[PDB]
Length: 166
Length: 58
Ligand SMILES: Nc1nc2c(ncn2[C@@H]2O[C@H](COP(=O)(O)OP(=O)(O)NP(=O)(O)O)[C@@H](O)[C@H]2O)c(=O)[nH]1
Ligand SMILES: [Ca+2]
Ligand SMILES: [Cl-]
Ligand SMILES: [Cl-]
Ligand SMILES: [Mg+2]
Image 1 (tube, helix red, strand yellow):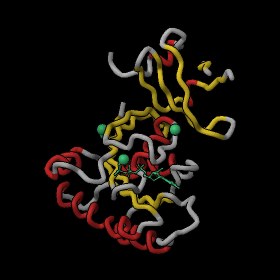
Image 2: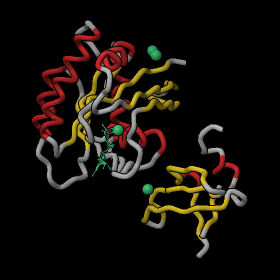
Image 3: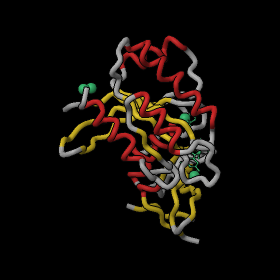
Image 4: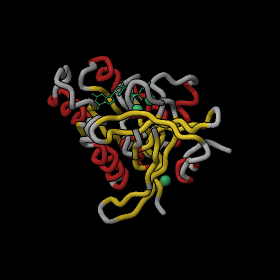
């Protein structure tokens, strides 16, 4: 069937693995659990079309920059994740974006901005800032919590919908 | 199905999130159940087959 090549990116500790493992296995990655780089497949139905998600859960610190670029070249769409209590990870977002555009050599790369850990009381990146950034990129914005599983399915599916729009 | 261990205790296989084999036993962690996450271990002898199937090759 149609496979979607999804890449989860973002700063160290934003919850790339926690999001991915919730989606794939319905577990929560706590501070003691594996968060190491790996790939995951899942068959899903989105808007009545069955498809396969082939998801790369990348390292916050990638060992080989040329490896990371080749990841991005192969990838059809990207979850750019930051944590809503980590302003650096949010400022790091544009960084990942430019890297993806430069490597892809294109202006319409499917992309979803993800603000994770929205379960936490102490937020330092409000919705408006992210929505504004997302607006300037022409991409959706989804709030998630890998802990409560809020928005987990939404984030990835919305990314698939984005690929279906070219 | 389920995994019986320890104070007997049952956790559904879907809740097992991490598992290895070592020293004749099978060691596992599991999600929130009865509202609390945790660990257990079962001898390799009395290990359910779908538990053992979660192990790494080979
Ligand atoms: N409260 C809360 N904590 C979260 C959430 N998502 C992840 N965490 C916590 O944030 C920490 C890092 O999560 P992790 O998924 O390992 O992040 P990562 O981006 O994969 N890190 P790395 O780049 O090092 O692989 C863990 O302690 C995890 O439990 C969330 O939605 N809410
Ligand atoms: Ca594909
Ligand atoms: Cl495709
Ligand atoms: Cl655990
Ligand atoms: Mg990780």
